[PDB]
Length: 628
Image (tube, rainbow, N blue to C red; front, side, top):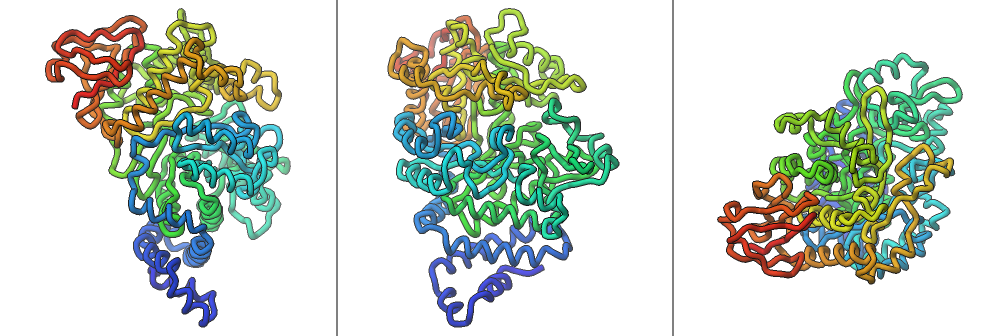
């Protein structure tokens, strides 16, 4: 195996002697040389564990690192400043100053120019982090909402140009906001150049995807594969027009990139350096578990998957230190955390907390949430959760059956109830959602619908507004980077007309992907409207979070409230949070509060609260009590 010093001199072997000597004396190279020394041994180890004695490994690595240097040389100087600043502050994502938003560029603002105009609103809201949904060229009609990529360099013409995006990224930075874009690295669309060329049998693109002659292999793989979109096709495979079969985990027009080929790693690392130099602060690592395949396994969460992500990480540490990773692993909780590490993905989605937030609204019982918060919340140093209430996706019930079992809960039966409840097929349910991917062969089902629809705002349930307040508070205060689905802050309901657009009617996730409601946004300043109540509620909690250092970091300790309806937890030995999940008044007992100070200021309601007597929370009330 080669070393850092060998590759460095081989990189400089493209320059003529005259220029080489000048390059070697420059600041850019010194930094690049330092980072090569620190981070290369990780890159080599990671790739070695995946590719072993592969013929192509060294030439690939030489080619990749030659680009890394060129990419870093061309890297805009203000991005280099961010590079140094994040090398020095690896914990910036752990700061209570961070509050994130996410929106579709078109549905929220028309296009990229219009998006840049909404920046003042983002500053009004207090956002420091903004995820723009898939921005790039994709097939017309059905494209899994942009997640089928036809080019990683060409912006969706309907949104604007590559130029506009750089302008947007720059303006966001001027406003103190980080740009977050998807890195859809598991798959491309079937109209992506690499797809067309691989399928056509271009030797330059051999083994870029998994294409089979017949059903022999697909049949054998399917024996152990999870079906993500069963509505679309069974198992993990789609048939071409020519009769062959391609690996398609998601839609049929989404082809799994083949990471057994090292040149696929190189190609995708090149695409990563490109997005980096655009000024992207955080890449959303889409479908992290899917990137490695092995016969007889579920082809999810395999060791090589982790290694490749760690290899990508090292690439950034070398050529773009500012670029952090956000892990999208919507899987078993034991597997979710395994992607979260400083040399893998520094942050990741927290599907466990989100799902249990909703669970608790339905059961009124905090047992699973409290369990999850007690045993699964705290993370390795320099890493954070992305805590959320809703997203562009369905809600999946991703609690651990093992964990449920210790509580005498049957996972199978509990998901039956949760699914019935949130699609308004359980007596008295306040929820107005729709099924997503009901699977007759597994019993599995997920839930589409906005936060407002799922808490009962559509029928004007008197508790709807408080429910939204309650959910966001937990996301904003547990510890980690909170991500608001833009639209929620004014109580945006479903697009009940999703099912009549024929590019959409097979994907109930559009129910909760409506176009910006201008009437609702006009009301955000009026406390008489639900939009206003929700807005000032959220805006208040954001303000408190960002200015009160009791919220800093990601560590939490659960407080046992001795009431099955009330969640309790402590931040930094100075903040005590209570959340009533009952629609009835619920009491935290004086006996329970014995060890707390006799009085504490509530950051929510503004009042001072007595803790040497019984504490009765109103329906869905949340208290943030300063106890130190």
